[PDB]
Image (cartoon, rainbow, N blue to C red):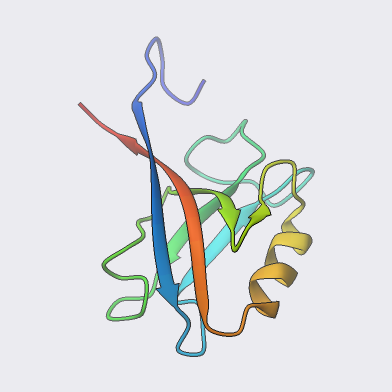
Amino acid sequence: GSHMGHELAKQEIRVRVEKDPELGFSISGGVGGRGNPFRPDDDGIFVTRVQPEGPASKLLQPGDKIIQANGYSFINIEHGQAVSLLKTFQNTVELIIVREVSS
């Protein structure tokens, strides 16, 4: 796993980002996708950057794993599909994320 001999606690969190009109964060990942620096063997979609003083600054953090966005599943999704879907979203994006919480 990502950590040697232990696994961090996980919290599922629901947040709403108001696009302004941009997301205010960047992603990487996906099945057969661009990878990620958090859980490198996990093919999920991860937040890689959060725009300072942007619409996600109080809500998201690097390393958050997006598992659902506006009712669409981001599990087994490809990078391009995730990017395309996020792009179609006009204003509010309701995300379900998994955040690792160190002890």
